Length: 106
Image 1 (cartoon, rainbow, N blue to C red):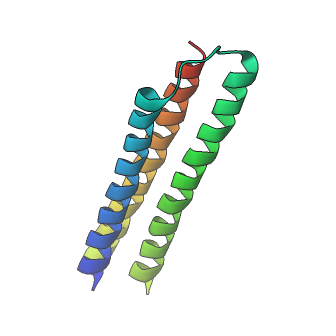
Image 2: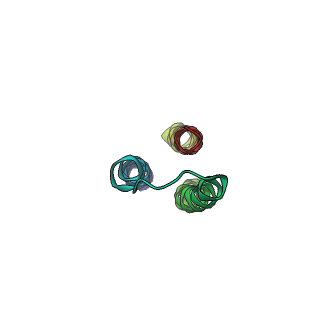
């Protein structure tokens, strides 16, 4: 049903968002203290970008599949809600990357 599809897509996006927040918390807590050379910063930035781009692939897949299922009344309200949730997740993922680059450039 459109109700189950909506609820499940939102639940999956919430899980991806929490995984991104937990990853960010783990960066600040578990990362080791070494000489922050230009090379160290570039190596860490490319890995963080790769990790966050893979989180974005998961969010994109959940959103595209939810929209596709809702396409095949209140169904339009659900599509708007899932798309708004996908956009906000994308902005949050972008804000994590920006804070991480600022954190490495300290």
